[PDB]
Image (cartoon, protein in one colour):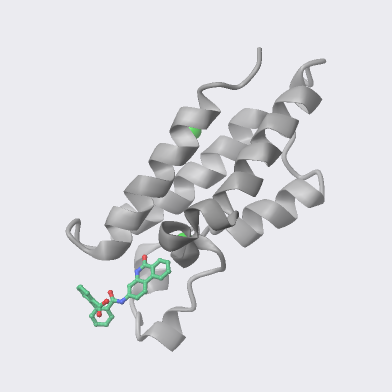
Length: 115
Ligand SMILES: O=C(O)c1ccccc1-c1ccccc1C(=O)Nc1ccc2c(c1)[nH]c(=O)c1ccccc12
Ligand SMILES: [Cl-]
Ligand SMILES: [Cl-]
């Protein structure tokens, strides 16, 4: 059920999203900007391993379209995106290092959400 704080909290989420997409973080955020194009990358097993792809452009579309009803729903998608990276890639891959850095940005600011 919607709470009177959900709009406020979703603004905090949108602020985080905007930060994740900003130039500040581009050196490590860029792999997460758009859906993984598995064929283009030669990742022909990606969609056998990753059942629920997620990326920041999809999170942005969902936010713009008011698809997210609360902050928890938003956070679950951002975390899904990172988990897909941790699932698919060896843990020493540079994309995993990038994901961990971007997730640290996310988690520290998400934990400042007004309530
Ligand atoms: O070549 C390597 O990079 C390599 C290095 C170490 C071990 C294996 C390989 C490899 C070997 C053969 C073919 C391809 C790869 C490879 O892993 N590529 C690749 C490229 C882009 C992304 C990705 C994986 N995985 C993501 O999760 C992802 C998420 C967002 C955007 C892009 C990517
Ligand atoms: Cl994905
Ligand atoms: Cl979660």
